Image (cartoon, rainbow over all chains, first blue to last red):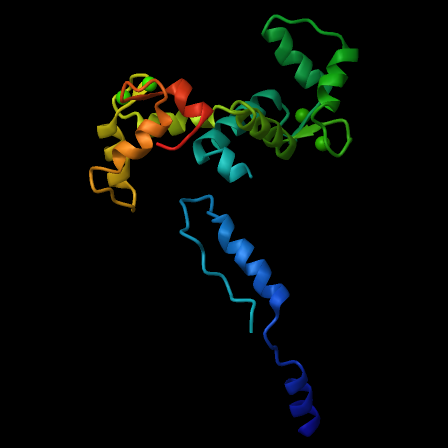
Length: 48
Length: 149
Ligand SMILES: [Ca+2]
Ligand SMILES: [Ca+2]
Ligand SMILES: [Ca+2]
Ligand SMILES: [Ca+2]
């Protein structure tokens, strides 16, 4: 029980600037899909 | 990607064209199959160039052309038609009427459709910057050299 709890706490994420920098460039591209056009798709956040 | 370059109708048309080459229906294009349709169109090539025009698009090197390779050929042909003419469509978006000049009212029309709004006075600010001649209209030549309006 406590080994599982300790392992889970070690896998908890914190603020990552490298991930944050990547997202800022990603949102600046303005991607779209093929079938139609998606307006800045909101796929899963990668910072915390 | 193929979905960007090709539509559902174009994929259907290409499949019919591929099936026209593949009389057997096995799913691959051989040299004799490719040679047969060329003779129907009048050309009488030799097997030396016939193999070369297959290897030029054959990706896996198996010596035969399947539908995935056939679509990849057509996808490139549709894509490479436009190289730098993208500014022509951009010019026509501002040029509603269809002539060779961009008017202030036409610039108002596109700006009205876009999110930002103008107070009917700063529209003259950027049009005079783009229009070097001073005639009040931005032509195609003035647009490509410097784009502000
Ligand atoms: Ca065949
Ligand atoms: Ca092949
Ligand atoms: Ca015009
Ligand atoms: Ca002019």
